[PDB]
Image (cartoon, coloured by chain):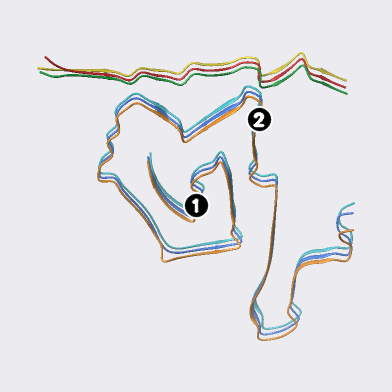
Chain colours: A cyan, B blue, C orange, D yellow, E red, F green
Amino acid sequence: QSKIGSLDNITHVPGGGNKKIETHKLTFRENAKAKTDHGAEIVYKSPVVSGDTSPRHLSNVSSTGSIDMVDSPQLATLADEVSASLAKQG
Amino acid sequence: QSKIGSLDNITHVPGGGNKKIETHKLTFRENAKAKTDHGAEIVYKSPVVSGDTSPRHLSNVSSTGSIDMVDSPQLATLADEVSASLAKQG
Amino acid sequence: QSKIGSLDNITHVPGGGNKKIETHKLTFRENAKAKTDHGAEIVYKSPVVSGDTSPRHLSNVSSTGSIDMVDSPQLATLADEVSASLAKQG
Amino acid sequence: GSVQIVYKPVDLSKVTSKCGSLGNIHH
Amino acid sequence: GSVQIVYKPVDLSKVTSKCGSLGNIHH
Amino acid sequence: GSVQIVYKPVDLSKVTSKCGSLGNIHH
């Protein structure tokens, strides 16, 4: 057994004239799992460059008025650029 | 027996004329694991480079008015550039 | 013993004219574990470089008015650049 | 006149052999 | 004449042999 | 008249031989 007579995730507002009354629940079990095993290989963002490269006069901008991140976690495995706002060259 | 007559994540508001009454529950069990085992290999963001590179006059701006992070943790394994706002070159 | 009739995470507001009544629980078990075992290997941000590299006149800027981090811990393993606002080159 | 000789080869040999499950017994 | 020789070979051998599970018994 | 020789080879050999589980018995 696990849960019986339980009160788990509730808003109860018998009153009047209230505003923005809120209740949040998030559960994360076993997310963002990598398993690489026996004789496997992962090759990630590691190119082989023998050619010559001349990137010039590049401009990159990320701008925002505001970022609100409410109850929004970031879980990352073998990832890189996990974000709310991104501006990217190459 | 995990829970029984139990009251967990609850707002109760019989009062009146109130504002911004909030209740939050986050649980994080075993997230963002990386297991690597036996003969396995991960090669990550490590190029082999033999050609010449000549990046010039590159400009990169990340800007904001504000960042409000609430109830939003960051959990990262073999990750790299995990963020709210991001600007990236090369 | 641990729980029967338990009360875990609650706002009770029977009074009137209140504002900003808040209640938070975050819990974190066994997150961001990395395990490397037997004959395995991880190569991470450690390139092999024999080309010539001549970066010139590079500008990088990270700017904000304010950063609020409430109930937002950072849990990093074999990560690197975990942050709120991020400007990166190379 | 001018002479420039660039010699920069790359060689990336990998061998990964008996990393499986071999001859193991279960009961 | 004027001379430059630039000699920078790169060689990245790896060998991994019996790094698995071999002949183990479970009972 | 000028001569420049720049000799910078790179060798990164690795060998890993018996780092698995071998010949163990569980009872």
Residue in the foreground of this view, choosing between B10 and D17? D17
Q: Place residue A37 in its image quadrant.
A: top right
Q: Residue at x 87, y 61 (%)?
A: C3
Q: Is residue D10 left or right of residue B40?
A: left
Residue in the foreground of this view, choosing between B42 and F11? F11
Residue D22's x, y, as percent? 73, 15
Q: Is residue C57 left or right of residue A73?
A: left
Q: Is residue A13 left or right of residue A56?
A: right
Residue C27's x, y, as percent? 70, 57
Count of picture labels: 2
Amino acid residing under circle 1: Ser
Q: Residues within 10 Å of mark 2 (few under 14, many from 20)?
A: some
Q: CA distance from mark 2 to mark 1?
A: 30 Å
Amino acid residing under circle 2: Asp
The C terminus of chain C, quarter of image: top left
Residue at label 2? C37
Q: Is residue B63 left or right of residue B12?
A: left
Q: Chain of mark 2?
A: C
Residue at label 1? B83
Q: Residue at x 86, y 55 (%)?
A: B2
Residue C45's x, y, as percent? 47, 36
Q: Chain of mark 1?
A: B
Per the image, label 2 sits on a secondary structure element best described as: loop
Q: Residue at x 63, y 45 (%)?
A: C32
Q: Residue at x 70, y 44 (%)?
A: A30
Mark 2 or mark 1, which is nearer to you?
Answer: 2
Q: Is residue A70 above or below residue A62?
A: below
Q: Is residue A50 above or below residue C79?
A: above
Residue B43's x, y, as percent? 52, 30
The N terminus of chain C, quarter of image: bottom right
